[PDB]
Image (cartoon, rainbow, N blue to C red):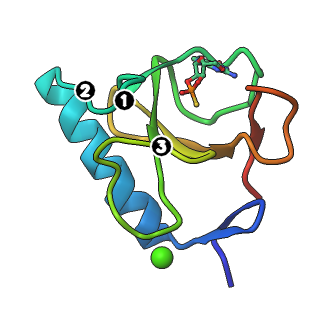
Amino acid sequence: ACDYTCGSNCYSSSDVSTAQAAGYKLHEDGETVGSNSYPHKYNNYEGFDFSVSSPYYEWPILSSGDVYSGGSPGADRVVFNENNQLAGVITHTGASGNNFVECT
Ligand SMILES: Nc1nc2c(ncn2[C@@H]2O[C@H](CO)[C@H]3O[P@](O)(=S)O[C@H]32)c(=O)[nH]1
Ligand SMILES: [Ca+2]
């Protein structure tokens, strides 16, 4: 069973922890990867009811199992805060345009 289901993509807690650690590391060092500069600030225009405090940062999580290192980020993202606390897992899949919906 999936801990997080983003459309057709299935993730475990390990997948999420691995992705988050990478993105948080880059955030801490003040570095970015990709043409869209990840990780970067996630404003939460959607207004998700996250259990942890802002600021939030988004980092791509890949269905391939690899850690994002550039190129197409896919539709899925892990959102974490300043304290490396997981806020949630969101996706563009099933959402209009560039909006997001939570992964169930
Ligand atoms: N939909 C959405 N995009 C945001 C938000 N904060 C920052 N963005 C960035 O704005 C871009 C347009 O939606 C998005 O491409 P993305 O790379 S997944 O990073 C997203 C937010 O709260 N909602
Ligand atoms: Ca996996």
What residue did someone put label 3 on? 72
The part of the image, by quadrant, that contains residue 1 is bottom right
Furthest residue in direction left, as rendered:
29
Residue 100 position, x and y percent, is 74, 33
Asked whether the beta carbons under mark 3 and mark 2 sit within 8 Å of each other, the answer is no
Residue shown at 36% from the left, 29% from the top:
39
Which of the image's four quarters has the C terminus?
bottom right
**In screen coordinates, is 70 left or right of 44?**
left
Q: Is mark 1 within 8 Å of ligand 1?
A: yes
Q: CA distance from mark 1 to mark 3?
A: 11 Å
For numbered disc 2, what is the local secondary structure?
loop
Q: Is residue 52 left or right of residue 18?
A: right
Please, what secondary structure does the residue beneath circle 1 have? Answer: loop
Locate residue 103, reporting x and y percent.
72, 53
Query: What residue do we see at 51% from left, 24% from top?
Result: 53
Q: Residues within 10 Å of mark 3 (few under 14, many from 20)?
A: few
> What is the total number of numbered labels drawn onto the structure image?
3
| Position above or below: 54 against 83 | above
Residue 12, above or below 96: below
Kindly check if marks 1 and 2 are in contact, taking CB atoms under 8 A apart as contact.
yes
Q: Amino acid at mark 1?
A: Tyr
